[PDB]
Every structure is written in structure tokens, then in C-alpha cells.
Image: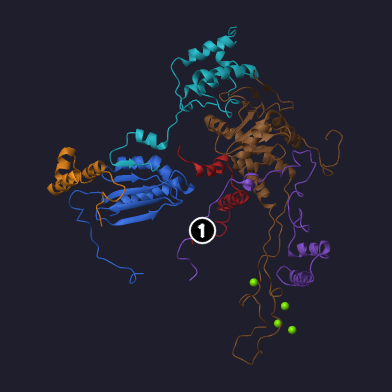
Amino acid sequence: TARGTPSRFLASVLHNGLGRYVQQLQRLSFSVSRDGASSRGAREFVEREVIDFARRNPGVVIYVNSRPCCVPRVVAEYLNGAVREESIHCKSVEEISTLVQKLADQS
Amino acid sequence: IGIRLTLPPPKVVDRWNEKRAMFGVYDNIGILGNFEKHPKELIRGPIWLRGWKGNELQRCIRKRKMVGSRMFADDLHNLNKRIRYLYKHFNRHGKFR
Amino acid sequence: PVRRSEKPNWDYHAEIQAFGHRLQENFSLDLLKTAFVNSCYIKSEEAKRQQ
Amino acid sequence: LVCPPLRSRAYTPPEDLQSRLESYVKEVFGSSLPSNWQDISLEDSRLKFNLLAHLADDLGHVVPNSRLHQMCRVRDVLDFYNVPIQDRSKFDELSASNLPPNLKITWSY
Amino acid sequence: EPVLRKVELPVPTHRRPVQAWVESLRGFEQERVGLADLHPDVFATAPRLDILHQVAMWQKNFKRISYAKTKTRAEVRGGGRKPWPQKGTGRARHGSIRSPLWRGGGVAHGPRGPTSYYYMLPMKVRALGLKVALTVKLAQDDLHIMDSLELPTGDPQYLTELAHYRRWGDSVLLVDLTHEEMPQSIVEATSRLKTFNLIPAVGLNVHSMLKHQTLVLTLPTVAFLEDKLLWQDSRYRPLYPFSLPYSDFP
Amino acid sequence: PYMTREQERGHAAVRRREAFEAIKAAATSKFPPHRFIADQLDHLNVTKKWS
Ligand SMILES: [Mg+2]
Ligand SMILES: [Mg+2]
Ligand SMILES: [Mg+2]
Ligand SMILES: [Mg+2]
């Protein structure tokens, strides 16, 4: 709902359009586990695409915990420090690739 | 409120004990035990069901005919009212007629 | 609040390297680390070293 | 009584293995009478046992229970051994890979 | 010396048998001593995970018998009278107490005494469930075969280190033909521990070998269930239960 | 009009016939889909786990 939810005027972070463009995604912190059937999407995503994702984006930094977790998580913070966590529980590798891609795209 | 503020204690789940380790054993005594016995006499349970399926009516009529003479008066009285209410129910009430 | 170094999932050398690639700059880490390091932290570093 | 150190499942084929196994094939079969020895068959279990038994204890790689029934002729055994096999955790091989500086992976055990 | 078993039953012309290694427990380092060809139709059946689903959960279900029960409004004590007049007061119409609405009243649709989920599958399906069970073990290299379950030391320490030295797994089964010919050494080991369980050949089932991460047989046992399941494959039409005698079948 | 009744009598009967036969082939082509060992055993891969 518009009235129940806050609002804002449209604005970019420090006018990233005129000057050199900078990928405004700072960090990605994956939380996977050596066990748990739900982590098949994240682990296979770590095998194939996270490598190429780093080669494509040298600016962004990536961390992987690989600890016991009943549900895998992925945490993403930006230059402004705005933390945004999303659940990748029981998701395909294709969905996770599009999910991490739009996270890299957004500010 | 229905929820509980504090968590419950973590119930330890022993996946390796006498029952669960020896679970499922001696079910194929007929298939590779030269058919000396059937797997239906293996199960421990009431005498009105040892290798047999039935609905609410079927299990009740089998009960009173077999062990009803040994049942209590109150339990036998509730049994007769049960089948009488369920006899008319399945016969008169419901769809498909 | 605290420093991000105090918070988990942090590697110092990898962050300045990944940071340098973010704003499209590439040069020696000796010049980078000398810029980020301040004189005040050296006072606390040697202070904690003695104590 | 005493447990010696475990054998690593990892195994790589040394050079001139074809000459090594071929020297033993001639030891089992006086001599290899027919030419084109690659198509020789192992219908008998004694021939297959003495063949595979010497290969394992000499090299250090055992054929599984799922594949020896597929190893009908000797060239199949040649293809099963010339291909390598490895044994290291995913953390070990990923760290061994040339990961860029920005990427890091941990191991909380 | 090697110990070879050649199949006594007939095999199809278009399916060759499958060889398998043989081991023992006299020594520690002793591995790959003897071979044994195996019938393909029972050791190379299709995966058929749906078959394993039915037969495995079947023996989870037919042995189950419930004991839950709820007293109905007739069974709960009281509730014979009418508490108040139909139009006398503002209170809602209620014929008695102990209805499903009132506190402490009986359930309308709840559990009814000890129920029975007993249902028997076809013998061919249950047999084929056993055929495919040890088959996938052979594909995954999960089972093992050996001459006999004798060992000189006879303790859990030697048994445990022997397992993960050959890299079998965490949980294992041990199979023998009858209940009497098990050596006292191996059985005293399995009694102290829990994981490396032991069962006879008659009690062999899919759920235990699928729960346990590996399997173990003996050559007399391999010929035993082979004769049974192939006899189920070439079986004659059952006119009556097999408990009664036959001409050739005991 | 462009054409007469008896002019346009039997000019499009070919298309209406072959078009209806295509509907017949579409109706007869009705069966369950094909099953595979691939899509059956991919469910086993849920327990794929690292060494
Ligand atoms: Mg009453
Ligand atoms: Mg009354
Ligand atoms: Mg009334
Ligand atoms: Mg009650």
C-alpha cells in the first residue's frame, strides 16, 4: 500500500550516470552448507556461475561461509551500507543466476 | 496467546537403537523362508485385527462378534450405539444415491 | 555500530583490491595501504603492542 | 591388531603402463599366441581374477564391483586405467584453482 | 586360494551374468579373494524407484496399528438432559452438554479406536522390490560378498577400522543363512555396537539395506535368495498358499 | 459481387478438406507423455554433496 509504505523522490547514488559508472553492489556473502538438500541450487551455483560472476565483475567482492545451515542465505550490502537479505531456499540454479545478476544491477 | 515465549528443549533423536535398527526385519519370512509362516501373524496387536483391514463399522462388528463377550457392559453398550448410528449414517446419509 | 573489519566476512587485502577494481583504478598496494593508514591508528597499534 | 595408514583413493596413471600390463598379459597367457591382443576376452573367472588381482596390488587402484562385469575385454581395462581419478575436497580444489583476489571461500570446520 | 562360484541356475542367452569381488574377515589387508558371477535379471533390473517407494513404505505401514481414540458426545459422561427451555431465554438453542461445541465435549470426526492400515502387496511386486534393491547396490558398489563371517580378534575396534579402511560407510548390514551357524566372535561384536547390524537371510528386507549405507552377504546366502527370487521369476500359478507341500518345492 | 454462385461452387473444397483432416490428426494425436530414466533419476541428485 502506498500510504502504509514510505516513499521517496527518485534519486541516484552520487550521480553515477555522468562520470565513470561504478557497480554499486559492494559485497556478496553467501551462506551455504556441506549438507542440507535445499543447498543444491546454491552449491551448483557456486561451482559454475560464481566463478564466472567474479571474472565478469572484478569490482564486487564475494564471500562464502560454507557452514552448517538448515536454510541457505545470501546477504548483499551496497556502498551506502544498506543491507538486503533474500532467501535462496529451494531455488534452481537458473533463478539464482538471474537473482544475483539483478542484485548486481540494482543500487 | 497460543505460542510459547521460550523454546522447548531440544529432543534428542536416536536414529540407531534396538527398534529402528531392527525395524523392517522378518517381513519377507514367506518369500525366502520356504513359506513356513505368513507375515500377518508377526504383528503384535489386538485379536480383533491381526492382518485385516476394516472401516469403523467393519472393525466394530468384528470386535463384538469375536471379543464382545469379554468386553465390559458400558463399552459394549457404547459399541451397539456406535454401529447403529453408523449403520444408518453410511446407508442413508451422504452423496451417491 | 562498529567497523566492518570487526564484523564477520572480511578480508583486508582482498577488499582494497576489489575496491580498486570498483572505481577503475590499478596501482601498487604499497601506495594504497599508505594512503588508507592514518597516524592515529599507529598510536593505538604501538600502544596496544606495548601494553 | 595393527592398522596401517589408509591408501589414498586418488590415483594417476604412470607412463608406459601399457608396457607394464602387456608384460603381465604375456606372463599369464606361456605367451600370447594370437596377435591383436587387445581383443582378447576374459570369459573365465580365473583368468579375470589373476589379471585384475595383479593390476590392483601392483598399481594401487581397484576396479569397483559395478565395472568389472563391464570389463569384458582387455582394452576396456586399458580405458578404465588410462583415465585418471582424484580425491580432494571441494574446498581444496577450489582453493587450488586460480581464483581471483576478490573471491574468497572459507571452511568453518 | 581363489574361491569361484558359477551360477547353478540357467541364464538367458541374450544377458550375460555380472562378476563381483569376494572378501573375508580372517585378515585385515585381505581384499579381492574370489569372484562370483551373478544372474543379470535380478542384479541388473531397472532402477524402478516407484517400486522401492511402495514396498519400502508398505512394511512401514501394514505393521502399523493405531491406538488413538476420542469419546463422542454419546460416550462422554453426561449430556442427557436439556440445560434450558427452547424459547424461555435469550441463550442459543443447545439440546444437551458434551456436544462438539461445548467445552470438554466429544469430537464429531476424530480418531476411532485402534485402526488397521494392513494391506498386502502382490508377492511378485514384493519379490521384485527385493530384486531391484540389491541391484542398485551393485550399481553403486554398496554391497559386498565374502566367504564367511569369521575373524580371530572379534572386537568392535577391529571391525570399525576394517570398515572405513576399505571405505564401506557408516552403517552396514551383515547377512547369514540360518540363525544357528553365526560364529560367536562376529555376533558378540555386533551385539556391543549398533551400526554394523546383523540379520539372517530370512529377515532380509529392502528397508534395512536402504537405511544402512552398505550391505554384506555370504556365498551360501547369495545362492539362497537367488534360488528363491528366480523361482519367483519362473514361478508356477498359485492355486493355494505355499505353506502346504508340493512335488518339487519343499 | 465478384463471382457468381455456380462460379464459386467448388474452389475451396480442397482447403476445407485438408484443414479438417489436420484437425483429425490433431485429435488422434493424444497420449500421455514419454517417460525417461534421466528425468526419473535426476531426483536422486538432491543429495549431491561435496567431498
Ligand atoms: Mg448420552
Ligand atoms: Mg432424556
Ligand atoms: Mg436433541
Ligand atoms: Mg474429551
Q: Give the residue type that dot 1 points to.
A: Met
Q: Chain E is drawn in which colour?
A: brown
Q: Position of residue B41 (x, y in %)?
A: 77, 49
Q: The purple chain is which one?
A: B
Q: Which chain is red?
A: F
Q: Which quarter shows the N terminus of chain E? A: top right
Q: Which quarter shows the C terminus of chain E? A: top right
Vertical placement of D27 versus A90: above or below? above
Q: Looking at the image, which residue is at 63% across and 49% down?
A: F28
Q: In which quarter of the image is ligand 3?
A: bottom right
**Residue that protrudes farthest toward the bottom in the picture:** E88
C35 or B89, which is in the foreground?
C35
Q: Which residue is denoted by mark 1 in the rendering?
A: F3
Q: Which chain is cyan?
A: D
Q: Looking at the image, which residue is at 59% across and 9% down?
A: D34
Q: Where is residue D41 in the image (x, y as percent from the top left)?
A: 61, 17
Query: What count of labels does the image hold?
Result: 1
**Residue that protrudes farthest toward the front in the picture:** C51
Q: Chain A is drawn in which colour?
A: blue
